[PDB]
Image: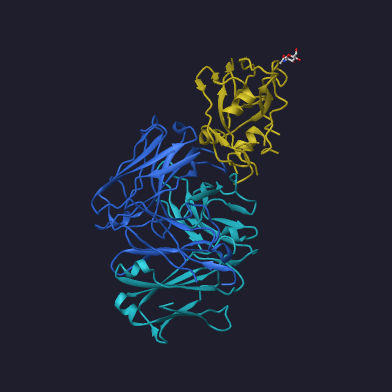
Length: 185
Length: 225
Length: 215
């Protein structure tokens, strides 16, 4: 059933990959056609935990759930503000596994400006993901959108194959952090 | 969150016009804009689109190159110039705003568009030379406590004409009939309304007839003889 | 250019039935389509965004489904307030071009109700203009199978009147038509009695409304 996006996020040696129930929250998977082409000639695929679930010392991840999703994705974590402050997260990870790793992440778009304050506190936020071959900076967009699949939010996901030895993450708000990663070979 | 379209009227075939859509309520610089026209009695037909930044604007092919679409995010309004109007362009023009997502529902996803805020729209009748104002006439009342009496506007061109009763006070039981095209080429319609016959001689009634293309506002009262 | 085809054009069902319409496409448009409701003389209103997803303000009766080529819109229990025309808009080529499909008009079937007949003489201000026009008025009836016959001095006048019927009402779903008989002031003052005979299905006997020009 579940499509490639829902399987990688969590809603066999073979060269054949066979309108399902995919993607709780509405959004898009950047470079979706490229990721599917890389999984056609997949020799080995496995999931190993990456950034820790409890690592978010000053950030809360127990409230990240959407009623249109029924909870949230298991591979990623939806970080919400703790108490009344949202400090800038500066998390980094270096690939210690021998095989190639696939790390994904997402950025959530709020409904309006009042929700942006009620969730991530900081008005102007950003999400900067850095690797050895990419330099991206994503700024979330806020606009009134018609409800899709139950709610009016949006989430834009990304991905990048990681070489041994480092992904640097930096976000000041509206950032769906990864909890687990996929190691390909 | 309200949209107001303005700039309609009678345009001779081969002339030009400009529509004016003013936005109010929502942040204007973050949403796309779309014009949609509706022929008299026919379905909806799309006209144009404009990006948030006034640099990307598609067209409806059938009217491509005939007229341009521009916007000004400062004045919080959307324009639509028109040139060389044919007879097939006589229609009511709607102004709507919609957000352009890129959601991926299903196996593979494409672009998704949805207009959620629509304006009233201004009728842009484009035909040969004519501009006759209305001549509102009265109708005297005559059943079982219910009586009817309504003004009649005849020999006017072009459409439309707005008929209000008691300056928009009474609204229940009002029946505004559609226009009838006469032999000479002038529209004509009647607007009646039923009221209790007990309050027929107590409360006064005056119909508010407004013809936007003729700049004629006639407000005559229905006097029972 | 994407081509949309909605069917059926017309539709008629009683208050409480299950009405459903289809809107097919000449090209695989995935789930990128929208549904709109336009009341007679008003602006369209967004109902369904991307097939199944709903927009705030729409009652729980409306529901859309489909994926790929053709799609379907189904109403749970048809209410008299739902009298409108329903279009479908493409979205697969949102940046370049979207194509609205020919909407499916919905009409309500009710019990036959007798019309309320009223007749109006020409205005005195109209006689000073030069012409004369006497209009017959019916209000709240069903169906539109009404036949109005103008009779002047017990002589049926033909080819001298026009009829105009209102759209189906939103509350009681009843029609109202008016037959305007226009003549000249010289021909108006020549006779003294004018009548309007109405023959409708809801009336066991045809109703007739007459008056005198003087009194």
